[PDB]
Length: 430
DNA sequence: ATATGACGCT
DNA sequence: AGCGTCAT
Ligand SMILES: Nc1ncnc2c1ncn2[C@H]1C[C@H](O)[C@@H](COP(=O)(O)NP(=O)(O)OP(=O)(O)O)O1
Ligand SMILES: [Mg+2]
Ligand SMILES: [Mg+2]
Image (tube, rainbow, N blue to C red; front, side, top):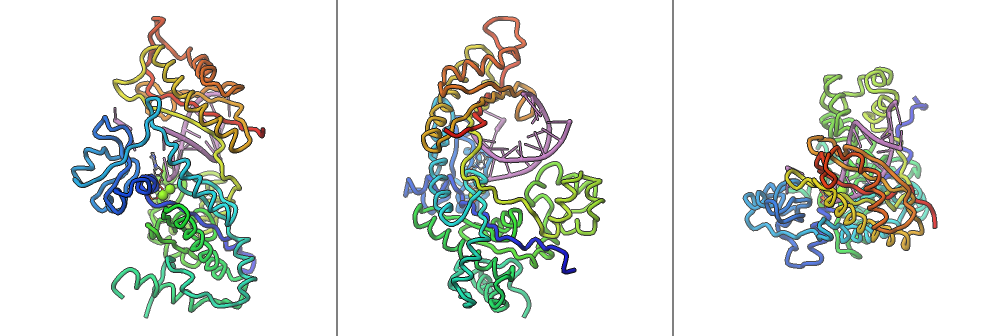
């Protein structure tokens, strides 16, 4: 009873940039600001594949994955910006550099774990402690929280959204024990105040807006972040979890969006995260394994222990390209040439990495996909990465995959290759 | 015919 | 080591 931990030990935030590639293009080109807008790669097939969408465009039903020509049928005024193309492939440098701007600002507040090109987790537990002693039991003003939502509030005994926001925040603050420095809810509130500040600094210094989740672990933080996007932050407290989870589809929780999530639904005959509570940990372990069962048992009670790993930099650097359908590489010369293109971008990125971050990759991984295999990768092999030299790197990769070629003729390659992928890995200090 | 990155399993 | 899962 007093021995049951509640997963309330930490304050953890997840910050995610609003329509990130779109914002990067909109900052560069004022003409695209406050417009239905999308970022697109490869204008040649159906106008390009959409990979990011402004919220004005979303309101017309434009989504990621969609072809640009089809997006124009839903939204004829849609403005587009194209991904840089270098060496015959998509080049994401602009967005990687924009990402670094954001991560450096967040780094100033606390230790971040970079989770994607546009998001990081933040462990606020220490910052909240320090901010709490400087505050000295002084009540927290709703003015310190001008973009914050308290999930599940307002409740009990207004028409438009900002009215509802404030009402819920007033209820939350009015209930707040500012007397006890170790109250979990109080810790979350102070965490929210800091994330208000962090998000203001990001906007001020970059022009980019973002949303945030503030809770006790990574999973709740990521879930909370999405609940009030764009340009808003959401606090999910321990106590909000039962109602929140009671109608929350299983697939919405991080790691349960694929096969395992589907098997939980299937095997257990449930739909919502909260329904998991009626199962014993041993029952869950028997159906899904020791670690999965353990993790589900605690998670459906809002408890999770994945720590925020102190890592602002990626652990691999990679370049890939699909060669779909009729463009699938079918000769030795095409394979070699495209491996050189990939190796050339890779080298440019590794040398920049070695100078910026005082480390060097030591292993090269080569990955291909062949026509008809619908796996991401058909095959992976590796070799030593000794020199940041594109010509050597591509030669080495060709060497380690050449024998996949099932062809009779010298100059032909079969089966045709639908993807090439070079990944530098196993970094070491230098 | 939609470019990446992290991590688990064996 | 090489493959399978899940993610943006
Ligand atoms: N399948 C994919 N292929 C290529 N790039 C992608 C991608 N998914 C995302 N990106 C790139 C482009 C994206 O801009 C960026 C961040 O991805 P999100 O945070 O999942 N989506 P956004 O930040 O745009 O919208 P909001 O967060 O407001 O919902 O990563
Ligand atoms: Mg985002
Ligand atoms: Mg994101």
